[PDB]
Amino acid sequence: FNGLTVLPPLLTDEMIAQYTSALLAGTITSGWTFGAGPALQIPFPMQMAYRFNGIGVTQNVLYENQKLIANQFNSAIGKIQDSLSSTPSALGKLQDVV
Amino acid sequence: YSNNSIAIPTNFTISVTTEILPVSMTKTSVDCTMYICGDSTECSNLLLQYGSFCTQLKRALTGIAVEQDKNTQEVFAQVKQIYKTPPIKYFGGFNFSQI
Amino acid sequence: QSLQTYVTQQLIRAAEIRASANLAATKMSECVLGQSKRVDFCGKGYHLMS
Amino acid sequence: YSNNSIAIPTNFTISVTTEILPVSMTKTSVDCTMYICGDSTECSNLLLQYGSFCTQLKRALTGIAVEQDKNTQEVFAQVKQIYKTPPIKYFGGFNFSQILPDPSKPSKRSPIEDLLFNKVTLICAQKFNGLTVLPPLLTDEMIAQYTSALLAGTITSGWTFGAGPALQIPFPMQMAYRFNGIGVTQNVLYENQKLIANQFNSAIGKIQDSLSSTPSALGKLQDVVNHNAQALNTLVKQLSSKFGAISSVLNDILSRLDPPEAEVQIDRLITGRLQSLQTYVTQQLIRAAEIRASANLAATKMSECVLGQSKRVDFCGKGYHLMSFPQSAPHGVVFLHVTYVPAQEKNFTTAPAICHDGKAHFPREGVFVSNGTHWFVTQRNFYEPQIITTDNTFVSGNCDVVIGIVNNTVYDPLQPELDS
Amino acid sequence: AVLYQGVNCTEVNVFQTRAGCLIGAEYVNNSYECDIPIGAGICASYQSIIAYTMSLGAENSVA
Ligand SMILES: *[C@@H]1O[C@H](CO)[C@@H](O[C@@H]2O[C@H](CO)[C@@H](O)[C@H](O)[C@H]2NC(C)=O)[C@H](O)[C@H]1NC(C)=O
Ligand SMILES: *[C@@H]1O[C@H](CO)[C@@H](O[C@@H]2O[C@H](CO)[C@@H](O)[C@H](O)[C@H]2NC(C)=O)[C@H](O)[C@H]1NC(C)=O
Ligand SMILES: *[C@@H]1O[C@H](CO)[C@@H](O[C@@H]2O[C@H](CO)[C@@H](O)[C@H](O)[C@H]2NC(C)=O)[C@H](O)[C@H]1NC(C)=O
Ligand SMILES: *[C@@H]1O[C@H](CO)[C@@H](O[C@@H]2O[C@H](CO)[C@@H](O)[C@H](O)[C@H]2NC(C)=O)[C@H](O)[C@H]1NC(C)=O
Ligand SMILES: *[C@@H]1O[C@H](CO)[C@@H](O[C@@H]2O[C@H](CO)[C@@H](O)[C@H](O)[C@H]2NC(C)=O)[C@H](O)[C@H]1NC(C)=O
Ligand SMILES: *[C@@H]1O[C@H](CO)[C@@H](O[C@@H]2O[C@H](CO)[C@@H](O)[C@H](O)[C@H]2NC(C)=O)[C@H](O)[C@H]1NC(C)=O
Ligand SMILES: *[C@@H]1O[C@H](CO)[C@@H](O[C@@H]2O[C@H](CO)[C@@H](O)[C@H](O)[C@H]2NC(C)=O)[C@H](O)[C@H]1NC(C)=O
Ligand SMILES: *[C@@H]1O[C@H](CO)[C@@H](O)[C@H](O)[C@H]1NC(C)=O
Ligand SMILES: *[C@@H]1O[C@H](CO)[C@@H](O)[C@H](O)[C@H]1NC(C)=O
């Protein structure tokens, strides 16, 4: 009413989601290479072996326990959604901004 | 703690955690004359004597407004190629349906 | 005076949000686009990805 | 994307990029009494009633002024010993004339520094009303000397001078160390030295041309200068406002009216000018905080990218970081990041492990690739096929645990030795 | 010592610096660390009071 207006953002939510989807696809298919140059494909277990070597654990640890690691990752990904949904104070900062 | 003893892990756990970070606030703009005086002409004439306060306020608000878009662009726009996932969503047992 | 108070508060909050956005950009650059050796920067434990 | 396919680079490119960071703003000082009142003494007596506002404003401005010098000292003065490049400017083909100081110029500045100085660009009116600007503690020549010392130290001694005494090292060997830093073996550089040097020189020339041919490259420092000048201009212009009085000039009010009403008129003028001064001080404080944050970022970048090699992604340029060079600019610093970028990738077929005699072999530092009929071990960042032996592979377990194992033979280097 | 900021020395041990006019300090060709910053590369210290040009650091030529 009194001469105050809210201006729309330049980036709509759909294009931000598109950016996030592009980042997810890049990091899933090409590991860390796409951030430092052209994207080079790599099988996901091999990328997992690389990242295991990155922290000081040999590749055979990943290769001989692939199913267990996959199951643990899937269980954590399942748990995180319920953790976010069941707690109202998880999103405190953005709601505080609003 | 001991003299010649260590503890070596024997088994592992994969953990997934969240981290929420605000990026941009709401871009807002104001009209100095309309807010302060409305449609009254005498009030506007009196307000003209104060000088360039409204210009300063408009400049600051415009700076904030452009800074918000700059923040969003810096945070998200970091790749100039729009990659696409393959049609077959199999990655060696890892399941990415939730993301 | 009311308008000036509002503008100053907006400026301070904008500075805070800019600091947060810079931190978020650094996190995206380092934890997502690569593997980070910094402790507790990208989660508790030894970082794998994000 | 696939699940038995990999892409390996076969060539590289040395890329140099620029990053501009503001460091310090203009040091300014104000005179509360002279600005608000001027030569009049009655106005000073009336202003004395309002308390200690002028003291607060002066203290805040002094704090900002000293903070600017602190920022510059933090960013640049990081080495307490100034180094000099050797007279013979030969570094194994690398050719640094565009960043080293130029003795011909009286100012002793590098050509890129000269271009940056030239590309960045009423005073009496501001000065005459109680507003002054203070000269920086460090002149431009001293900043250039600091940058030259840092550059000579990083050229002659690598990263060793940043963590203790400076130890000399031939430049190709330093490049080999920095190549080992990113996971590429030394023989690559020792065999492509000429190509790498040519690429580096071409990149430096392109950097100079790109900086010269674009006017919007240095927007941040110009924005700082424009902000300071515009704020000062607005503060000066605020003196012409009536602020509800009968005249905007104090002398006419004093010489036209009686004291009982002259006091009211000067009261209106005093409160208006006090509000203007407070607004200016607050804006300066906020801008100083932002500039301090930028200066801290610049100091961190100088400490980590210049005085060493950084593993952080995109912190010191796009790609795998190799090294960096500092240059001074009006109210800021310019970093030239030299980085390594893979190119000319190629398809290959890969396997996680090799099964041989019921034993699983995994690579030590490379990856298994196949060109269609034979299997080799290569580095991840550069294609260099090698015969699979027991030197580059290690054994763990049997062939049935892992998924995707591939049959092949593993050469024994000692087999011809004991056989002969 | 007294420093008149932004004033030529002819409009007021007299020294003319880029910051202003300095009275009560003697200029010395020697260089030391900065003790009391004055500006434009000029610093003052007490040893009487002297004014000098600050030294960046010890010279070192790596072989
Ligand atoms: C390492 O931990 C995982 C779980 O964190 C263990 O996996 C469990 O093993 C038990 C016993 O076989 C099963 O009943 C569970 O179903 C398993 N859980 C999952 C998620 O697979 C694993 O056994 C541990 N390692 C060792 C050597 O015991
Ligand atoms: C990946 O995860 C999704 C969701 O966690 C799984 O989809 C579930 O499949 C079961 C059995 O078909 C259904 O009962 C659930 O309702 C599904 N969930 C959702 C959210 O739709 C999926 O099976 C998992 N695996 C793969 C390979 O996609
Ligand atoms: C790797 O790339 C470099 C340049 O990017 C190639 O060198 C070029 O070779 C062609 C043909 O021999 C010449 O015309 C160019 O002048 C060379 N460039 C430079 C900068 O000298 C090199 O041949 C490539 N290597 C491979 C194996 O493809
Ligand atoms: C290092 O780079 C400089 C600048 O690119 C080279 O200087 C050029 O040399 C040629 C031939 O002597 C002249 O025609 C150019 O005018 C020079 N450029 C400038 C800007 O003066 C230099 O040759 C390179 N190598 C060495 C060893 O100095
Ligand atoms: C895959 O690479 C291997 C290794 O270079 C190739 O084997 C050699 O091929 C060349 C020419 O094709 C012959 O002259 C050599 O005698 C081969 N060496 C051996 C030990 O056999 C192989 O030909 C390549 N395969 C393809 C399809 O290009
Ligand atoms: C890799 O080589 C092993 C050993 O030669 C193969 O294992 C044999 O496979 C045949 C046919 O399937 C069986 O009759 C034998 O009993 C297997 N022997 C053992 C010890 O398991 C294996 O099949 C080969 N894999 C591939 C993909 O060719
Ligand atoms: C390593 O040897 C070199 C000789 O090439 C030494 O460099 C000389 O050191 C002396 C002693 O300070 C100086 O007076 C000379 O000016 C240096 N020569 C040059 C060309 O600069 C160097 O000091 C030796 N380093 C060690 C640790 O002994
Ligand atoms: C073991 O501990 C004792 C005392 O707790 C100490 O004197 C001794 O030095 C330790 N062992 C070694 C090898 O130092
Ligand atoms: C590998 O990919 C093919 C097709 O993309 C698929 O049919 C096959 O099942 C995958 N490998 C495994 C072990 O699932």
Image (cartoon, coloured by chain):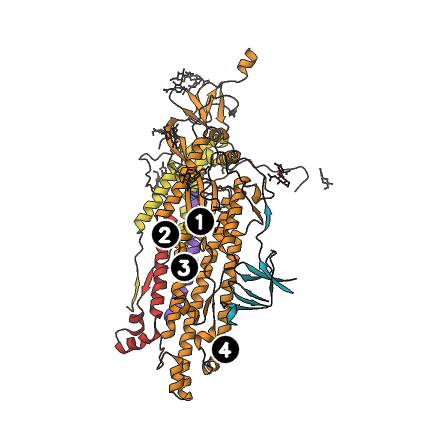
Chain colours: A yellow, B red, C purple, D orange, E cyan
Q: Quadrant of ligand 8?
A: top right
Q: Quadrant of residue D348?
A: top left
Mark 2 to mark 1 CA distance (whole Å): 33 Å
> On the same chain: label 1 and label 3?
yes
**Residue picked out by circle 4:** D51
Q: Residue at x 47, y 72 (%)?
A: D31
* Marks 4 and 1 in Cβ contact (< 8 Å): no
What subunit carries mark 1? Answer: D
Quick one: label 2, few (<14), some, or many (20+) residues within 10 Å? many
**Residue picked out by circle 2:** B72
Q: Position of residue D175 (x, y in %)?
A: 50, 35
Amino acid type, callout 1: Glu
Q: Residue at x 38, y 41 (%)?
A: D206
Name the mark nearer the viewer: 2 or 4: 4
Whether D76 is drawn above or below D274: the answer is above
**Residue picked out by circle 1:** D113
**Residue picked out by circle 3:** D225
Amino acid type, callout 2: Thr
Q: Closer to the N terminus: mark 3 or mark 4? A: 4
**Disc 1 on helix, strand or loop?**
helix
**Disc 2 on helix, strand or loop?**
helix
* Marks 3 and 2 in Cβ contact (< 8 Å): no
Mark 4 to mark 1 CA distance (whole Å): 49 Å
Whether D245 is drawn above or below A9: the answer is below
Quick one: label 4, few (<14), some, or many (20+) residues within 10 Å? few
Q: Residue furthest top?
A: D420
